Length: 60
Length: 286
Length: 286
Image 1: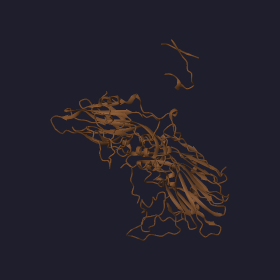
Image 2 (image 1 turned 90 degrees about the vertical axis):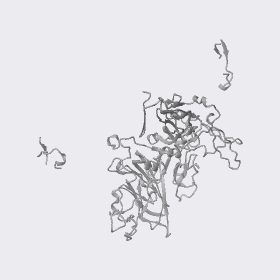
Image 3 (image 1 turned 180 degrees about the vertical axis):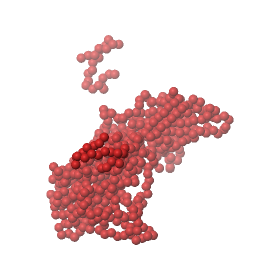
Image 4 (image 1 turned 120 degrees about the vertical axis):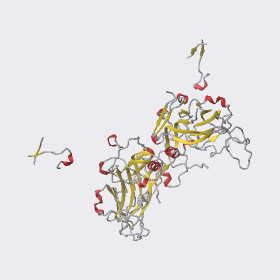
């Protein structure tokens, strides 16, 4: 985050495995994997996307 | 056979029934299932009554069949809608487990079984700037019963109006009795300074609670165990907890006459289990 | 470094890759969850390939997140519809897990997750009198692929026509090619004596199977483990098993010209587990 030190907010970072409709509202995205990012002294957030696959490898 | 005690004096029991006898803190991270929460301005967290949620033990189990424990499929954080805090707001309320009745597999398990129990983790989020002022009181009430809007009948609130869902309800500053005898509204009329149930708001701090003060913290966390007079019960008939949010000090910003900020709620079931599988329930919610 | 063997002769490996190297019985009772089955005229039961269903082990798990195991909530007997066996019948087929897509919490878990796996117990029921004659062959086929109804295109069966659900499909005695180029039907045309896939029916006994002979037994039981080239997969895209029922000897009763008897199917998932929770899938099934 590259705003002023006087700004505040909270964000939602979401990952959804395939098979259903892609999320377009926070209501749908809230059902998959997600992190809630609170912007404070630490200005960075990390979200890990885990390996969830049916095959052992994926094509590029 | 006499019992000697001190005041000495002597007592004897005459009957076979005992009834007859004469008598660092700012930083927080939570992880449930595939969901995580982080917080950088917290006021610690509250565990209601000093008891953590747990599963039902064999020495306290009423039903005899094998229970269902979804775990990660249902023990996860769900985000409800976001409300707007302005200078005219009086407060909001929600019922648990009523607010999670349409939340993924938790709602499905709730409506497919006959008995269920669970604890909760509640996380309230509200942030502003260093030039805002205000305070919110968040209270968790066991058996949160609200008063109706009728002065000719009592306990006449309909099942639909008492279970609003994830949208919840709001408090009001005045009591307005309903006078339509032909088409009664049959809904609550909760007054803020009476906490909606005839008791003074100042004493609501007997219940588990926290305070969000805009100059100190921006989030609140409450951990609620399962509380009831039964080991397990029907989740569709009876609500175990109620969440009430009230402005203790009105919101104000610089010199603007209409400031506003959002408030968000996230709730996670904990150690939930179910009994009595059958066909699904289809309630009349409208 | 040479290897000496017998035919003696000597061999040496030149390359670092190994690829380069030169080369009582009648009585039965089943209990799952809150469901039970009894049988008094059985021909024992069949465990496919001699392998019982089991959960996925750590040394063979592809996905890294915590799986969901509903157990009793989904591992239970579900009864499908009942078909009518007459003298004009050619046979019926079903796909698994396609036939249980609307069965209690099993279907909900199936449509809420991205990966799933499970075994099955299949119980076919058909009873008659001591004056009826006939025989049914019940076969379980892994990767039961059926042929289409078009001679101008191949592999053109639509997703809707290949997944009928708990109603299933039927075999036919003749092949009728579809000739509507403007509005192709895009459906299977399975022929009974070719088993619907171009192979002779007489050899279908290579697959796991049983025979219901009306003068011997009245039920059949097949226990199917999970079979696939992957440890876990998508249950909504791919069907693991197919069940085929065919009359080996036509039904006949005394001298009546139109006898008929019902056939019922009951299927129970076993050791089912799921991965990859998200919002629910809403397929186009019509």
